[PDB]
Image (cartoon, rainbow over all chains, first blue to last red; front, side, top):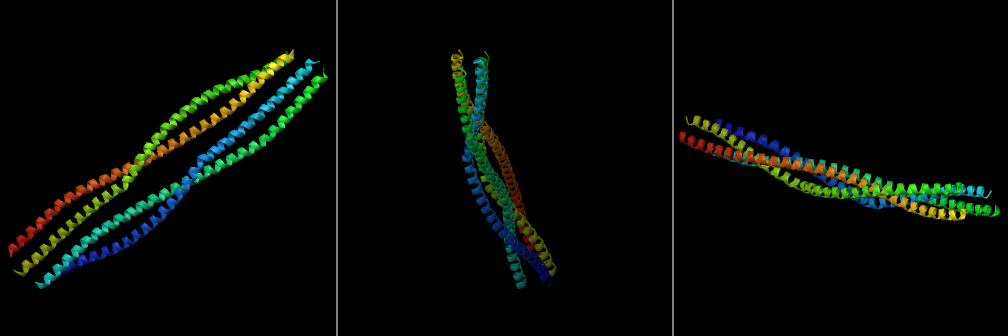
Amino acid sequence: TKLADVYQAELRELRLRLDQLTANSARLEVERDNLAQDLATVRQKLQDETNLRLEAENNLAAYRQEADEATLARLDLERKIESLEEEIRFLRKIHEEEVRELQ
Amino acid sequence: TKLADVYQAELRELRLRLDQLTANSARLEVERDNLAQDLATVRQKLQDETNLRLEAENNLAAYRQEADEATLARLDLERKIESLEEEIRFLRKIHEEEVRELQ
Amino acid sequence: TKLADVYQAELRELRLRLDQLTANSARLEVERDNLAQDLATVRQKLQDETNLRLEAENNLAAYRQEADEATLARLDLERKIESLEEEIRFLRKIHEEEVRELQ
Amino acid sequence: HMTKLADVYQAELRELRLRLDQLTANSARLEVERDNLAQDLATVRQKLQDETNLRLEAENNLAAYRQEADEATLARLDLERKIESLEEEIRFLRKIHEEEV
């Protein structure tokens, strides 16, 4: 009986440990399955957002050129205006002087 | 003797299973740790790629708006130019006339 | 005459502006040439550093697996050690019992 | 009198104005190109700094994983010897016990 008790003691311990490990393993498998599903989703969200970023960044260079050329055209015209208003003022001074000389 | 033999057999089996289950559990914990790490990583990449997308889209919007402002300003200026050129023509005509009369 | 002065004044202003603009344009040409050379340099450095970053990031997953497998192997052995020490303890208990039963 | 002079002066004025219009246009264009090159230079310098930081973190994690593998392997080797020692001990215990009966 003492022999049987020694054996049963070791058996009982091993069965206890085994039951705890099976429980722990089942819980870990559930958590792993969940993390994997969420990882698949967020990877898809990343791919989508990368594609949108990429298209936007591609359009940028052409739009920057459009803006530069439009701004350059505006400036050219503002300068022509300044030139014409300068020309007018000069004409009036020159004209006023010429009419004084004919008196 | 038959009894000890049944016990030693079960003892050997349980130790075999236990070693496999411990290995399996260790592996699962490693897999779970990895999935969690990668999930944190890709979530960060998603956030980054969203921020870059938004900034790109904003720069696109800004370049379109600037061009529009430049084009509208240009058109307004072209009309002021036509006005100034008319004014110049009228000034020369009036002055050429005044010059003829004073002679 | 005053008329000649009016004309010479406008001429003087235009010439000075032209001189100022030519000087500024020469400066700007130099600065543009420099910015372009440096831009080419830093673009090359960027490409190089991107290639290294990319290869490092690619090797990451493989090195993490190497570490995981090495750690898993270690654990398997530490467990086999515990198994053998348990077996020893049990053998001594069983042996002591058998020795008592056989006087 | 002034007619001769006015003609010469108006001609030079016309030339200078034409030149100013061309040079002002060119300068404006150069200013735009310089502003752009500077902007892009700032951009790519930032990308370089970012890419360097990512490279360094990656290389650090590589280094750390290589250290983990080396230490784990060394521990494994030490354990395999302890295993041999324990198996030797077991065999000695069984032979000594079998003798004692």
